[PDB]
View 1 (cartoon, rainbow over the protein chains, first blue to last red):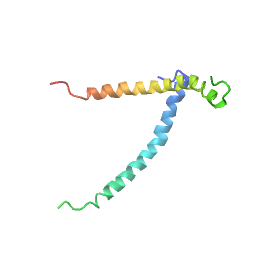
View 2: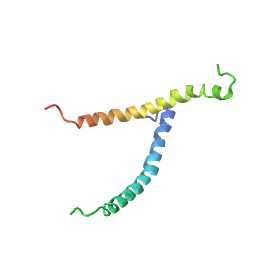
View 3: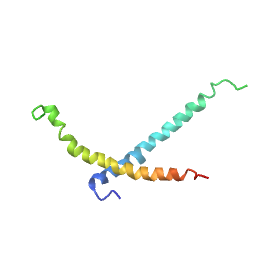
View 4: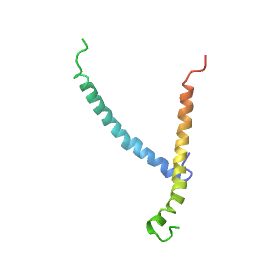
Length: 49
Length: 49
């Protein structure tokens, strides 16, 4: 319910274009890249014996 | 008294229309979110028992 005024109507749909279609594509390749090293760099830790 | 100094007179009536609007336009989407999240998360908390 911000689609009545043009100023806060344009503002609300600029969110979704960034979020659903451009920010969401980055959070996938930032998660899989994070989960890449975080499983890699715990190998380099000494055995806990 | 900046009427004639080009740079200082430029930013004088920038903030009149650009900041009574956008900060207010920022004020809607933050107040829509925060009242939702905080009241969700204080309801997540435990009562005094």
